[PDB]
Image 1 (cartoon, protein in one colour):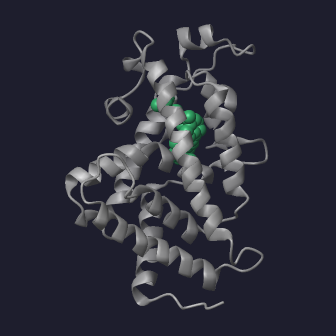
Image 2 (cartoon, rainbow, N blue to C red):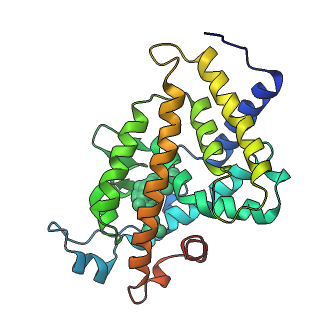
Length: 254
Ligand SMILES: C=C1/C(=C\C=C2/CCC[C@]3(C)[C@@H]([C@H](C)CCCC(C)(C)O)CC[C@@H]23)C[C@@H](O)[C@H](C)[C@@H]1O
């Protein structure tokens, strides 16, 4: 019923997050040519043996993800309150949410036209098959695609998109956090901003119920995170795999 207006601070928080995102997410994907080149071997049969022997798309996707983790670190440092946390808690939050924020931010390149992440010409269009060529299986990929479509359908305003990523990163329920109280205080400030924004800026149908759907996406990410971790583990058993990854990727998922 009640629709309180966004406070001055809440307006500032949103402005800061929008700016942070615009500075860390290049909608033209102009840096991609700097990554090791994508290579797509003939694997129409989806052979795990072949996929693992070649890992043809791993160097490229590993670079794409490493590059993205760097952008996410930059985004997080601009989240109001994040710097108030200890560097130790900052690193714990970053490492545990990295893959989740990547999945969330990737929704901007994802398209329902053909269910792919389109980041330019054909070379930088990623499909389910490109992900299997990087050593992952459908157990992760299919739920990931479902998640992307579910997120697209929420038709989030950019304001809601950046707030969701911030809330995802500043979660008090991450293993190893020391000052959960502070982290939760910061998250609540963000969650209240989102709840308030939805109530007085998001037109129906969806003026309500949207918050719950967004929180549910965060739960969905936890599942995807666990499945990715399990699969990364398997991938790391492949001899010479480390050279196809990056130091940052090795640390974050190691
Ligand atoms: C990164 C991005 C991105 C797309 C994301 C994709 C497509 C290719 C596969 C990938 C990277 C999956 C894949 C399951 C993760 C595999 C990583 C390793 C190999 C380390 O286990 C997670 C998100 C998805 C492009 C831009 O949106 C932005 C630049 C974003 O940030």
